[PDB]
Length: 50
Length: 17
Image (cartoon, rainbow over all chains, first blue to last red; front, top):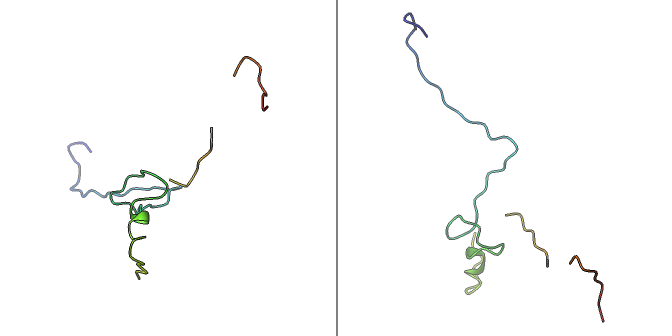
C-alpha cells in the first residue's frame, strides 16, 4: 500500500468446513423427490452397470 | 435431501368412534 508499494501477485482459495460435497443421481441436479428420476429410469432393462 | 417425511384444533378433541 501507499506510493512505495512493491509489485504483487494475488492468491485465491476458499474454505467450506462442516459440509460434504454432493452429486445427486438426478437427470438435472435439482432434488425433485427422494426417489430420483434416474433412480427409476433403468428399472426397465436389468442394468447391472459397473 | 437426506430422506425425511411424516403424515401431518382449539375447540376440544379426541373423537375416535
